Length: 125
Image 1 (cartoon, rainbow, N blue to C red):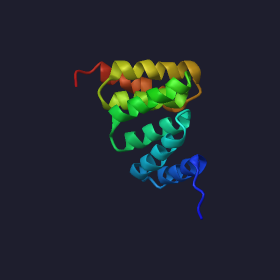
Image 2: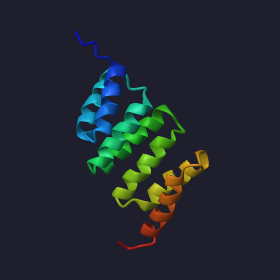
Image 3: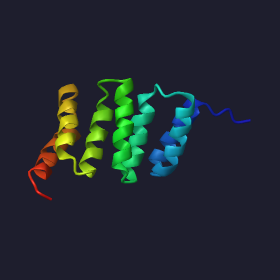
């Protein structure tokens, strides 16, 4: 029957992401972590799924796990910055955002983030 592998789970996980069903994507990607935990793509996308469920603290850790595998993964920094921002950790987020700017200053999204997070940090809210 269906020969679902790490790659299949990755693909089906991507489907849930595009379907905006990130809570199910978590399940798919977590099954990948039963097979292989050296894939920062799983963590970075799982973190994204957490971000959509407002689970920033979880997403932060998944992004770290991604960086543990690949020290320089822009996806991991950017989505960790998003996580930190959601946890009101603006100083922390700026560290990851600036890091993204160092690795890939071509990312317009990041240019909008570090400007925003600084204003949040400049607020007492």
